[PDB]
Amino acid sequence: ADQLTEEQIAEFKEAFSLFDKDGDGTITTKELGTVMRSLGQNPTEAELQDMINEVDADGNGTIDFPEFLTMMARKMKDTDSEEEIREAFRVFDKDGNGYISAAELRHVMTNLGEKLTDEEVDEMIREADIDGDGQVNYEEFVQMMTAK
Amino acid sequence: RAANLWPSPLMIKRSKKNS
Amino acid sequence: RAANLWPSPLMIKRSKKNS
Ligand SMILES: [Ca+2]
Ligand SMILES: [Ca+2]
Ligand SMILES: [Ca+2]
Ligand SMILES: [Ca+2]
Image (cartoon, rainbow over the protein chains, first blue to last red):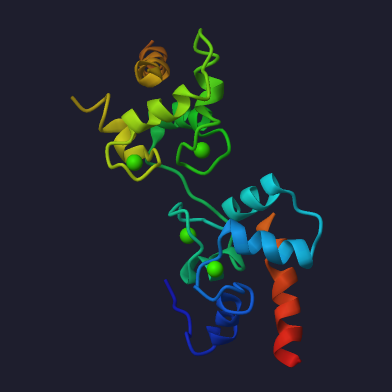
């Protein structure tokens, strides 16, 4: 719905150069931590990480121009396809970003009966991730156990 | 491998939701 | 959060563009 004038948003593109600092067109935890270190001196290592997770609304793990506008405009997320798995997902997601990072299972698996070690948390998702992108999406989640 | 643990919570959820 | 922090250096960016 609607559109955005790329010509007018060109002023915001300056954040993909000056804000970026390195000039690669992608805001990552490194450059962000650099800017926040000189013009901030408050956000910790874990802070800038969570902060970036507060920007990435698509879950691609990379700050892109399209989501830049979304972050600075409408912070709302829908949900209505994961019904049953949602009951499980809300507990499996923990942080609330859809994809499984690692820390989430470190809670549900440790509360599963045994204790989940951080060394096995990588091996487990590497078995879970059928695509091999490094993340656990709802797609592969249902297309693994429920889908025979 | 905790992989088998992946289906456990999900299976338990399915069972609980089916119950 | 991001929406508060992002506009902060963004504001400095405006100042840099004005400089
Ligand atoms: Ca960059
Ligand atoms: Ca993104
Ligand atoms: Ca998550
Ligand atoms: Ca995946």
